Amino acid sequence: DHDTEVIVKDFNSILEELTFNSRPIITTLTKLAEENISCAQYFVDAIESRIEKCMPKQKLYAFYALDSICKNVGSPYTIYFSRNLFNLYKRTYLLVDNTTRTKLINMFKLWLNPNDTGLPLFEGSALEKIEQFLIKASAAALE
């Protein structure tokens, strides 16, 4: 489809500019995700691809994009990102510096109680696997 193509390319183009913790960009990507749920899977793959491809510090900001979309838009993104969340998170964690790791850890903590709703942001399975991994990395308690 034409409109789909344009919207997806526009999403990717903006995402390429996420080289730092840009509030305007993250918020703009979240609004695009809210307004084009029909392109959700395209946005998910674009973000997961960026997290996997880009380098260390930039991987965090792409995860902040993923975080904003899930916390503010919710479904179907919370469902879609849940599938590769653990592998993506663990791989990123293993490839970034320790300061970035504390940021990934704080982000994970808020996924357990997003917006103080008392309901985990993602599939319980993904979050438990991430918690186990963090414990095995001396990064979460129950050491």
Image (cartoon, rainbow, N blue to C red):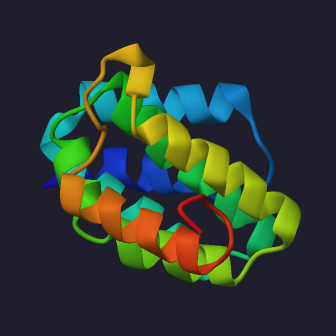
Residue for point 36% across, 65% down: 85
Q: Is residue 49 above or below residue 82?
A: below
On the rendered image, what quadrant is the C terminus found in?
bottom right
Q: Nearer the viewer, residue 79 or 136?
A: 136
Left or right: residue 36 versus residue 109 is: left
Residue for point 17% across, 35% down: 75
Residue 117: percent from the left, percent from the top? 31, 17
Residue 59: percent from the left, percent from the top? 66, 65
- Count the numbered circles shown: 0
On the rendered image, what quadrant is the N terminus found in?
bottom left
Q: Nearer the viewer, residue 3 or 123?
A: 123
Residue for point 58% across, 44% down: 107
Residue 3 appears in the rendering: no
Left or right: residue 7 versus residue 53 is: left
Left or right: residue 8 versus residue 134 is: left
The quarter holding residue 19 reads bottom right
